């Protein structure tokens, strides 16, 4: 190449880890007999997306802010065609910080708690966006925890209670006579202002569980026919 | 003959080769929390215990032809030793660095290579991927736990296949952690100085293993017929800058 | 001027945009940072650390510690090849799972130089000579010890040194995607091969089989570009771990 083309800005922490990814998709409805189908929930975690988890786990401790963008689409269910009228749907995205009240239905009071920040969003606008700061009581998040959550027979190995980042809840904001609609929400995740400590070997084996490091034994690399190099 | 030096800490003395190199983990020497002794020290006083600064020598292990490796979980490896072990019971919070010596007793007629590595937060996987490891499978204090050559199938045990290092990574990549190689034709000991490494300034020493010491033979032991059939390996630990929560009124 | 016009691209979501975002918790005072040892600023710091190469990735040796060790028998083999592999640290089965290799599989293009360390783990009484031959890209592996000696090479005397270090230039990616079908042979990459100059000899009490270990890391400033998804994760996006 040219006289000094040596570039490594793409392997900096921010460019390695600061890429918006789709970490969860789910649906909720305006009308249903089953109450749990009328709202959606998601505990904020990176451990259920394999590609992000592997990259994040080359480090032991981390600090970052999180930027969340919501891509929300809706469709009409199959029902009576008299409701050709489509008043524009409004949505509520609720962040519940660590320690906040959690809703049990669409009618729970926790949808109105002044300490759960919410976005109210109507279809046809730019997608809603919200940022969450660094949320731990401790000084860093931990990707690995070689300990027990508490001293009991109910302690969980590898569970650090200080990695709690909150939850997100989704429901329609209905008027008196809503129609039957289904909405799918895609959550987009971006890490900001990332710091990391104590690098680790990349994960070799397949991920088995979202909550621990369990693995099936895997060979260190793939095989070749001979140890020597032969002139083809 | 090579120069040797004697080190006395408290009421213990060991000898080391002056030509032995020391690995300081991440280049950081252990120290106290003194840099942040502002107002927080009034509502959260801490006290040192300098009588924990002595050499604790564990039970030696025998490096054999069929040996796959050993590991020791720390703080936990010293829970039954002395004033250090007693302080783990009396103080709810603590922090400490360490000086670790790993020495081999081998002759010039023995061959083999070991990796000595200190792995912070060495979370180990279970031998059944739908279950969870019991505490006894992770450590038993002073007694060393062993790796195996291949996969095991214990119900609640550790997956101890050595080439995955019980963590699901390629064992050849463990040089990213503070480490020293022992090649029996060039050297027979390793010294690693470990600072305190955690996401919080202090923690409970019975609940959390801060790091794990691993001794893994990459090249197996071999010798001629009639020679000693094993090489003893001795681990010696000296806590550095141990600090605990205060027990007095404000 | 207060009166404005909205341009194409307004109200769209570009996943690589960089805009100021509204804060959900503006009253929250975050935990102050504390010094932690081992802070990482760039992924090339990982790649500059030596890791063991599984040179003996043949047969069942990948399912044990034998992949990492190269066997050398005493009293045999003068003039024969001990081992060899192409110089493709990203795509070859020899290098793809090392610290350097896994970092390089996250990028579509890279270039630099690699540092190779060879360690003889035999007894202090075992002596012999090895030829470490380097073939530049486009040349192909040597066929005999004479051809290896006629090119770039280092004579490694394990009776004098336990270690030998090679710094190999002109290392660069060869394909836009992962092409391991040319994994054994790359027409754009060179080779390193090891030859018996002499056999390994010893006294009667050091007749044991000996081993060589190989280490690899990025030698100097290594360049990477075009971050991509690593090919070592598949079918797991569907399984959700």
Image: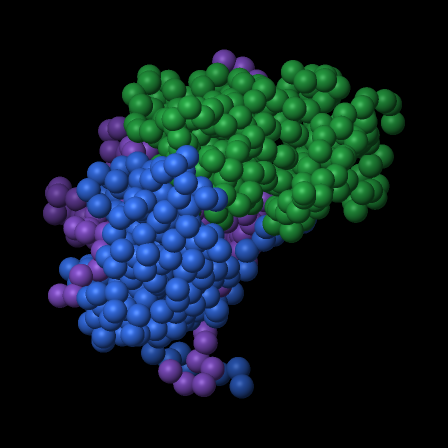
Q: Is residue A113 visible?
A: no
Question: Is the C terminus of chain C in the top left, top right, bottom left or bottom right quadrant?
Answer: top left
Residue C122, x across and y down, in percent = 42, 43
Instruction: Indicate whether B82 appears above or below B240.
Output: above
Q: Considering depth in this image, is C95 or B157 the residue closer to the camera?
A: C95
Rendered location of residue B108, percent (x, y)? 51, 37
Q: Which x, y percent locates residue A209?
A: 34, 33
Identity of the residue drawn at 76% across and 35% down: B6
Residue at the outermost front position: C204
Q: Is residue B65 above or below residue C36?
A: above
- In the rendered image of the structure, the colour used to display chain B is green
Q: What shade has chain A been given?
A: purple
Residue at (55% x, 43% y) in the render: B187
Q: Is residue B16 toward the left or the right of residue C220 in the image? A: right
Query: Looking at the colours in the rendered structure, which chain would you say is drawn in blue?
Result: C
How many dots with numbers?
0
């Amino acid at each position: 190449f040219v006289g000094g083309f040596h570039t490594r800005s793409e392997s900096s922490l921010e460019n390695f880890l600061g890429r918006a990814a789709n970490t969860y998709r789910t649906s909720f409805k305006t009308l249903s007999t089953k109450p749990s189908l009328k709202f959606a929930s998601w505990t904020i975690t990176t451990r259920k997306v394999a590609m992000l988890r592997r990259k994040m786990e080359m480090f032991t401790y981390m600090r970052f802010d999180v930027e969340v963008t919501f891509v929300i689409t809706s469709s009409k269910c199959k029902s009576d065609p008299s409701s050709g009228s489509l008043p524009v749907l409004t949505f509520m995205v609720q962040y519940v910080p660590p320690g906040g009240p959690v809703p049990s239905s669409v009618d729970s009071f926790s949808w109105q708690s002044s300490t759960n920040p919410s976005i109210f969003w109507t279809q046809g606008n730019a997608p809603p966006r919200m940022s969450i700061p660094y949320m731990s009581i401790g000084n860093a998040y931990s990707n690995y925890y070689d300990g027990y959550s508490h001293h009991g027979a109910d302690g969980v190995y590898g569970y650090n209670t200080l990695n709690n980042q909150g939850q997100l809840y989704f429901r329609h904001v209905n008027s008196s006579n809503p129609g039957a609609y289904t909405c799918v929400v895609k959550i987009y995740f971006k890490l900001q202002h990332v710091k990391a400590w104590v690098p680790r070997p990349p994960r070799l084996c397949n991920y088995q569980r979202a909550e621990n490091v369990n693995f099936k034994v895997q060979g260190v690399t793939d095989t070749k026919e001979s140890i020597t190099a032969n002139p083809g | 003959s090579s120069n040797v030096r004697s080190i006395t800490l408290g009421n213990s003395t060991i000898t080391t080769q002056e030509s032995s190199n020391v690995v300081v983990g991440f280049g950081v020497w252990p120290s106290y929390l003194s840099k942040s002794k502002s107002g927080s020290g009034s509502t959260q006083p801490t006290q040192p215990d300098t009588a924990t600064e002595r050499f604790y020598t564990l039970e030696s292990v025998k490096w054999q032809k069929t040996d796959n490796g050993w590991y020791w979980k720390f703080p936990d490896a010293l829970k039954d030793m002395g004033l250090f072990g007693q302080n783990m019971l009396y103080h709810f919070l603590g922090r400490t660095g360490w000086t670790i010596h790993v020495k081999c007793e081998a002759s010039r007629f023995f061959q083999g290579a070991l990796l000595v590595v200190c792995v912070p937060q060495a979370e180990k996987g279970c031998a059944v991927i739908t279950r969870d490891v019991n505490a006894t499978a992770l450590d038993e204090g002073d007694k060393a736990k062993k790796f195996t050559a291949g996969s095991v199938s214990s119900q609640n045990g550790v997956q101890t296949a050595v080439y995955n290092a019980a963590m699901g990574v390629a064992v050849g990549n463990l040089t990213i952690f503070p480490h020293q190689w022992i090649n029996l034709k060039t050297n027979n000991s390793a010294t690693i100085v470990k600072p305190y490494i955690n996401s919080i300034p202090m923690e409970n020493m019975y609940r959390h293993f801060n790091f794990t010491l691993m001794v893994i033979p990459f090249v197996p032991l071999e010798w001629s017929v009639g020679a000693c059939t094993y090489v003893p390996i001795t681990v010696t630990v000296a806590p550095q800058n141990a600090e605990y929560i205060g027990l007095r009124l404000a | 001027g207060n009166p404005t016009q909205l341009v194409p691209g307004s109200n769209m979501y570009l996943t690589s945009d960089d805009f100021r975002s509204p804060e959900a918790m503006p009253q929250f005072e975050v935990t102050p940072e504390m010094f932690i040892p081992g802070e990482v600023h760039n992924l090339m710091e990982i790649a500059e650390t030596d890791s063991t190469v599984p040179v003996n990735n043949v047969g069942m040796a990948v399912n044990s510690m034998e992949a990492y060790r190269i066997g050398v028998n005493p009293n045999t083999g003068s003039g024969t090849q001990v081992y060899g592999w192409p110089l493709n640290p990203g795509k070859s089965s020899v290098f793809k799972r090392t610290n350097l290799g896994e970092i390089l599989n996250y990028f579509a293009h890279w270039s630099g130089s690699i540092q190779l360390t060879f360690v003889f783990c035999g007894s202090a009484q075992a002596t012999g000579k090895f030829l470490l031959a380097y073939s530049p890209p486009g040349a192909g592996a040597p066929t005999d010890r004479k051809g290896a000696r006629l090119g770039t090479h280092v004579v490694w005397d394990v009776g004098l040194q336990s270690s030998c270090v090679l710094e190999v230039p002109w290392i660069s990616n060869t394909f836009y995607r992962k092409d391991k079908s040319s994994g054994t042979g790359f027409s754009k990459a060179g080779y390193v091969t090891c030859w018996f100059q002499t056999s390994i000899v010893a006294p009667a009490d050091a007749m044991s089989k000996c081993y060589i270990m190989c280490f690899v890391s990025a030698d100097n400033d290594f360049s990477v570009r075009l971050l991509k998804d690593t090919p070592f994760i598949k079918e797991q996006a569907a399984r959700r771990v």
